Amino acid sequence: MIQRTPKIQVYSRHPAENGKSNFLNCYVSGFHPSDIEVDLLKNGERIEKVEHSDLSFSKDWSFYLLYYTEFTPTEKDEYACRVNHVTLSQPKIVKWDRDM
Amino acid sequence: GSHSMRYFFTSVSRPGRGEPRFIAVGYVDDTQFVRFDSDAASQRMEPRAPWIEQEGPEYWDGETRKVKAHSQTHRVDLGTLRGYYNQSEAGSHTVQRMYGCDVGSDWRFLRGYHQYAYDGKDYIALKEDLRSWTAADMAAQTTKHKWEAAHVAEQLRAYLEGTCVEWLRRYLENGKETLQRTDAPKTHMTHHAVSDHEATLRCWALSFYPAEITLTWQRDGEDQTQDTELVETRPAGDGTFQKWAAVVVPSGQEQRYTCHVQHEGLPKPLTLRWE
Amino acid sequence: YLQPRTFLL
């Protein structure tokens, strides 16, 4: 095959405001092959109830998926997306930064 | 504006036996309206938008029969391609397939598509005239010759220029309240002093639909690309999309820089300045 | 509306 590593973005559906309900998003794209392991983390620990979009692909045939879950951000709590893929030595953790 | 209907199919084989994964997604423009996923144990083509949900039981029965036929098609194709490439049953391989049609502002036919990839690279594609094929390698040439002799492109052209556009028009009418409206980007700019010597300007575009947008930076009215970063347009999860573009500027020279936004939902292109 | 015909690679 030809193997392509995922791009990863972690972000919220709406501009984040402490104490107000929101959605945490982990968008992975540009990867091949399609099998990929995506986890949303709260304070280093995997969130268990997570939804995802239906796998689709772009004009270069590379795949994309959205993983998301309900969350209420506080200023103390930390979030991240953890991604594993055959192109990665070990899982890549991308921290949620609300200005990004 | 213009509109499209597109179906995206992914088929992933599993070592030896074990059923392959099969997933089918249908879109109008950037709105998903149907899905079937073997990994989610689907048994029917399932609606994902209210304008398609109102279609009756004969419609859904028919789409369910056809999506099961596409699944079996791909099960054959995975076996066929292993033969063409002399590949063992132990490895995992991927077939992707996309097809559909574009219409214009008058909703008349613009272009049709029907194309395949194997293991992440082009395999065969219907050319723009919908009469001939581009084959990527020698295995695909076998497919091309077979499909030429059987007059496949002529059959597909009838679907692409006819059935597809005809059902797209119907979808666009039933979903007029959602499908035929645009959401202009909500834009703003942030300034983060990186050092005493530089500052990052980040130009944001939020809650827009369709996903197509352009964000570009200018320095004193010329296009500037060095010291810039541009992320992929990303889904918000509520049907809209987001994007940002950033540039690192010398502190004190913020006013040389302008962010430009083009989107189908805007009356005119936007110019944003840090001020 | 899916294609009603089948063509195999």
Image: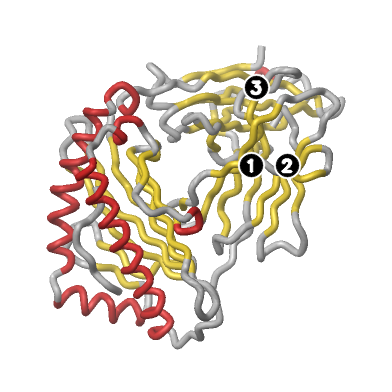
Quadrant (top left, top right, bottom left, bottom right) of the C terminus of chain A: top right
Residue that label 1 marks: A50
Identify the mark nearer the N-term, 2 or 3: 3
Identify which residue is drawn at 52% across, 44% down: A53
Q: Determine the chain carrying the residue at label 3.
A: A
Q: Quadrant of residue A52?
A: top right
Distance from the alpha carbon under mark 3 to that under mark 1: 20 Å
Q: Point out residue B106 in the picture as x, y percentages from the top left corner.
A: 17, 31
For the residue marked with disc 1, what is the amino acid? Val
Taking the image as shown, residue B92 lies to the left or right of residue B147, namely: right
In front here: B203 or A72?
A72
Q: Which mark is residue A47?
A: 2
Residue that label 3 marks: A15
Above or below: residue A27 compared with residue B116: above
Element on which disc 1 rests:
loop
Identify the mark nearer the N-term, 3 or 1: 3
For the residue marked with disc 3, what is the amino acid? Pro
Q: Point out residue B117 in the picture as x, y percentages from the top left corner.
A: 41, 66
- Kindly report which numbered mark, 2 or 3, lies closer to the viewer in this rendering: 2
Badge 2: few (under 14), some or many (20 or more) residues near its Cα, within 10 Å?
few
Above or below: residue B84 compared with residue A10: below
2 and 3 marks on the same chain? yes
Identify which residue is drawn at 43% across, 35% down: B212
For the residue marked with disc 2, what is the amino acid? Ile
